[PDB]
Image (cartoon, rainbow over all chains, first blue to last red; front, side, top):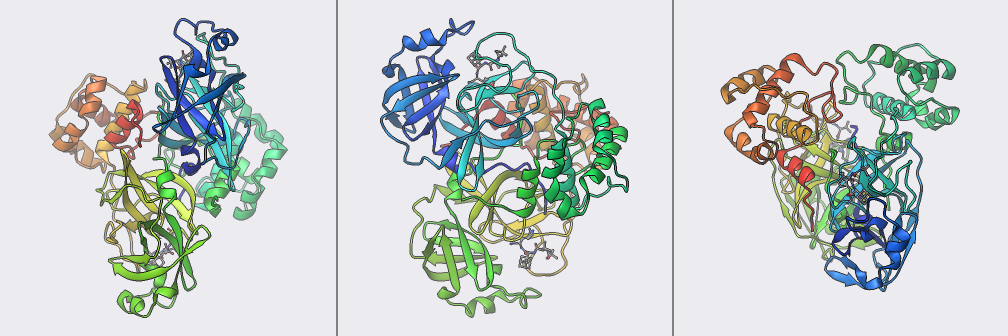
Length: 306
Length: 306
Ligand SMILES: *C(=N)[C@H](C[C@@H]1CCNC1=O)NC(=O)[C@@H](NC(=O)[C@@H](NC(=O)NC(C)(C)C)C(C)(C)C)[C@]12C[C@H]3C[C@H](C[C@H](C3)C1)C2
Ligand SMILES: *C(=N)[C@H](C[C@@H]1CCNC1=O)NC(=O)[C@@H](NC(=O)[C@@H](NC(=O)NC(C)(C)C)C(C)(C)C)[C@]12C[C@H]3C[C@H](C[C@H](C3)C1)C2
């Protein structure tokens, strides 16, 4: 029993992190086969970031402007190119610890683990969700750019996020591993802000199921509601609307607990309207929306990774 | 910026996990050099655990009663012995991925990362604290015994916990890596319960500093209090008493924020007496006590590991 904010084991990713220096700027890079992926703003100086012109900036660089260190070993850069907001550095050595991997662009609501890194060295791992406004609520200090987010499916590491910047509200924005930003952000020093965030409803329900699986039942009631009736209440409190795909996704959890999704929705409606009254659920005094239905199944039924 | 429940990167530990089978029982073991460490109850059958007699049970076993798998490779067991509640299985091959390591018995209030495992395979990593009643609030399913807790100091992995059992309140109990239980528990199927828990005061203060470092200042006030005055209020709400060592430990955080420990204590006194009134701190509606002062420094100043 028990329920924790649980991250994926990070070993397979730790062996792919390297340090990348261009000029005075050092950040992290991801070394898979003979390519090192990193944020393209490593080729910038302070005079550039007002409105950098990355095509020009990259044409003025040569392979020897790039210092790549894997631990103590220097890697020789034999080619470079730009894809959207990422730089790809061809190196002369293929990473012998390259795991089976793929690049995935995730959807808001999905979760992933972040391996926070500084100077090529792993500092810590934690779990977070892509918010509906395409930010994540991370923990990042100077030098953290190029840190990656990932999932593990059976044996395949799915990379989905590379860190680029922090917004004035203290949240974080980055790209997929092909360099496309999540959300409307750009890699320039210009004023940007996240849109308003909403609560991920399907995830709150998944977490209520986890609570039931673990013996926190005080919020259940005998009522039912309809999708239409529930969604009307949801938008009033800034919750994402619930869809039929969401209902179907929650199926396994409904099955294991014997509570129908629409039953659970009437409990959630209740909690929105009267609050929790100093009671807690799974140790929290707030409704938690950073566990997906698959996260709950994984942690309450025990799937491992190879 | 940002603040997350952050675990240590798990790569160095993942390479030491193995599967251990004795008879019908399979659990996890820790393979360092040529020794595999695992809970001694792997030598039990259901008929035994009422009141097992482990000396007798172990004398009736031979080296070939133990099946150790590292991935697909079987390891040959060439010796066995018992130390307190752990079994040590000498194997014929030394683990080539053995990190620099040590065994540490931690104190209540300290935190560590748990690498939850099933059948020798890492399932996920999360952070938790030794509670004052010598339990941890973990997440463990059948087959999880032998999963280990650890810290990383510079390059050395410090193992401090091996998982054995779950108590009726849904919390968890285990041993250090020399087999001594934390707390008054024993490895038998007999009625056991944890003592009453208390809140780890020095950790709540460390987390209030983290909040200030991250811009949550609404709970500060201009008052000060005394250790004696604060501790009197603390015991009323089931908080650990604060000591002068605690004050000294909080020194770096006091220094970086300019708020004196005794200032911060008057804010905490305030929060105990009037609550939070629907406000949050660092995204939480409860006072959080599972971050040590060192955890806050590590995450708000950026230390890495090699
Ligand atoms: C990566 N190393 C770092 C990430 C930052 C550092 C602290 N926390 C983080 O997440 N990247 C940067 O230095 C970027 N700058 C910031 O994150 C920056 N915020 C900021 O200027 N925001 C707006 C106005 C929205 C652009 C602070 C340091 C937090 C104040 C970038 C990354 C690239 C694009 C852009 C210009 C530079 C190159 C610096 C932001
Ligand atoms: C290890 N594989 C497993 C850990 C458990 C399984 C589910 N969650 C966990 O943490 N160990 C056990 O099966 C132990 N049993 C329990 O944890 C058990 N609780 C229990 O009986 N508690 C008291 C009454 C306090 C002993 C449940 C499965 C949760 C109901 C042990 C481990 C060894 C000592 C003792 C007898 C057996 C050998 C089983 C408990």
